[PDB]
Image (cartoon, coloured by chain):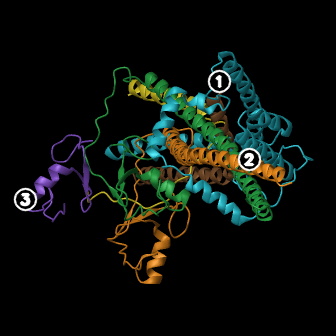
Chain colours: A orange, B cyan, C brown, D green, E yellow, F purple
């Protein structure tokens, strides 16, 4: 977590009731007394005695420190890795289908190219023996 | 512009090109027109691997000269092919055809590129899987050595910051236990 | 072999990501954890001050 | 009804209104971030704020099976399904690579065929011109 | 609906350790953490 | 997943965009025809 105005962890986390943004009481008392109760970043007017509220952290549950080995962190890592791998698979299938579609087009145009090159080979051939016969006959 | 654009579209191709074997296969092709097509294709692979060296490709490959041509008659040839177009197949039809191909030869079989449609030899299939598995296992211990070396490097880089976290967690646990004892004492003392 | 290849490739990618952008994340995590340590410490100190106040007054 | 990106029922469904296509919100926003706001399958841009439309319906009652009423079976099920999905990803990547090589060889044959059509067209044209000159020089009876 | 007020913060980053970079490492961490916390729950029940 | 009118799987699913609510197409068409273009649950005008 980060405080908004100071960019750190607030010693006394106080919540703006109007917008729900995390503040620190001393810096925002400074801000309101030097800006006439103007919320930072917005045009809203904030009330320190009614529109501001601190944070109470009950310590009933034994607090697990935020480490990556923990099960909430591990399941967030699992769903993030699943997100990345599924989007990679989805992309790969997208240009795979694109490549297969232009592959079908490429195979059909290769068949057409084979047809026209057979036709042009036969045409060039019959032209060549026609020229040969004409040169033989024209003595 | 003289060079082909089909290999300019990267789509990782072979670094090694055998002009002799390719020309031998092209000459051994029984169809004359397709034989000429494969021969000029072999010349094209020789030209590509000669004047465009891939990383890992051997250098000093000899290029092959090609007679010059004109783009107008190139467009004329393309117009001949375009008027020899039949009806284009539907993308759903192509997808169904390739899905039937996948079902006949599953994802591993189509993933292995050594499975031609004429290769019914079980021994040749086993040999292909054996060669592919040997190359795969080569990749396994190469990437395993790389990953183990990098993990050891980052371990020796970050273990100093790793050691602090356990002590800080222990201090947090002691603090929470002391806080629970203090609040229980607070309630008990204030009532009494 | 292919499953192990994909797993090891993902492991190497995460290892490279931790090499290039892991130290700042470790620093900010340790900083947040010690901030929570400071919060628990001031809570216990406040309760101990309450005990000290009650004991001296009584 | 399944999501387009995963082929599964999305946990939080949204709808692209431009084509009326179901998507999952987190996957589609991550895709837009990676691809600079490009709708999958098409070229047109996608708006996750306005064009996306969530679906409010009843929750899907996925049955919890008696074999998967125990965390060892859950762990081996997740293990085998993750192995199968990552093997599917590796096999479709190898399929894309091999079909790219096949299309490379195919287009090598294609522009080789274009060049042979080119050369034989030039040879046919010069043969026709030479034959026309020969017939002009000769006296047809 | 009304008395609940959300906060607007950033994503708190948990640093991935060097050992837990592979999926099998994450899975064995999953089993180890599951064992540790179910043991904690059990021991909590009998100490209560 | 279920339809909001019959509680079954819609063969031709449609969504009212103004409320983002799934309906079956034939059922929502006949309901709008019967009740003069009014979406179920709401009092706004739904265009078929």
Rendered location of residue B173, percent (x, y)? 53, 40
Nearer the observer, F42 or D19: D19
The subunit letter for the residue under badge 1 reads B
Q: Which mark is residue A70?
A: none
Q: What residue is rendered at 45% in x and 81% in y?
A: A33
Residue farthest along the top direction in this orientation: B123
- Quarter of the picture containing the C terminus of chain A is bottom right
How crowded is the residue under tag 1: few (<14 C-alpha within 10 Å), some, or many (20+)?
few
Q: Mark yes or no: residue C16 visible.
A: no
Q: What residue is rendered at 47% in x and 77% in y?
A: A31
Q: Which label lies toward us, 2 or 3? A: 2
Q: Which mark is residue F35?
A: 3
Rendered location of residue B115, percent (x, y)? 64, 28
Q: Secondary structure at mark 1?
A: loop
Rendered location of residue C6, percent (x, y)? 63, 35
Q: Which mark is residue A125?
A: 2
Mark 2 and mark 3: Cα distance apart in space:
79 Å
Mark 2 and mark 1: Cα distance apart in space:
36 Å
The subunit letter for the residue under badge 3 reads F
How crowded is the residue under tag 2: few (<14 C-alpha within 10 Å), some, or many (20+)?
some
Q: Which residue is mark 1?
A: B119
Q: Is residue B51 left or right of residue C30?
A: right
Mark 1 and mark 3: Cα distance apart in space:
67 Å
């Amino acid at each position: 977590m980060l405080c908004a105005l100071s960019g750190e962890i607030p010693e006394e986390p106080v919540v703006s009731k109007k917008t729900g943004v995390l503040f620190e009481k001393r810096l925002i008392l400074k801000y309101l007394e030097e800006h006439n109760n103007i919320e930072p970043g917005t045009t809203e007017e904030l009330d320190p005695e009614t529109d501001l509220l601190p944070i109470k952290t009950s310590r009933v549950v034994r607090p697990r420190p935020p480490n990556f080995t923990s099960i909430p962190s591990l399941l967030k890592a699992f769903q993030d890795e699943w997100d990345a791998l599924v989007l990679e698979t989805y992309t790969t299938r997208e240009q795979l289908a694109r490549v297969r579609e232009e592959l079908a087009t490429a195979l059909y145009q290769h068949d057409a190219a084979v047809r026209v090159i057979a036709r042009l080979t036969r045409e060039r051939d019959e032209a060549r023996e026609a020229l040969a016969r004409l040169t033989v006959t024209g003595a | 512009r003289r060079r082909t654009q089909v290999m300019q579209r990267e789509l990782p191709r072979t670094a090694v090109v055998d002009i002799d074997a390719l020309l031998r296969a092209a000459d051994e092709i029984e169809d004359p027109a397709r034989a000429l097509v494969a021969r000029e294709a072999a010349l094209l692979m020789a030209h590509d691997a000669a004047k465009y060296p891939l990383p890992g490709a051997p250098p000093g490959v000899k290029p092959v000269e090609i007679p010059r041509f004109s783009d107008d008659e190139l467009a004329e040839a393309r117009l001949q092919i375009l008027m020899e177009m039949k009806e284009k197949p539907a993308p759903e039809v192509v997808h169904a055809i390739w899905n039937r191909r996948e079902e006949n030869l599953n994802a591993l079989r189509l993933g292995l590129g050594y499975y031609d449609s004429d290769s019914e030899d079980g021994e040749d299939d086993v040999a292909n899987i054996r060669a592919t598995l040997e190359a795969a296992l080569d990749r396994l211990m190469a990437s395993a050595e790389k990953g183990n070396k990098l993990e050891k490097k980052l371990n020796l880089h970050l273990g100093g910051y790793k050691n602090r976290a356990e002590m800080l967690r222990k201090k947090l646990g002691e603090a929470h236990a002391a806080l629970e004892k203090a609040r229980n004492a607070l309630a008990g003392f204030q009532v009494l | 072999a292919y499953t192990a290849q994909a797993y090891l490739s993902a492991r190497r990618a995460h290892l490279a990501l931790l090499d290039t952008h892991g130290k700042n994340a470790w620093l900010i995590g340790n900083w947040h954890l010690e901030g929570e340590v400071k919060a628990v410490e001031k809570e216990l100190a406040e309760t101990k001050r309450e005990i000290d106040r009650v004991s001296l007054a009584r």
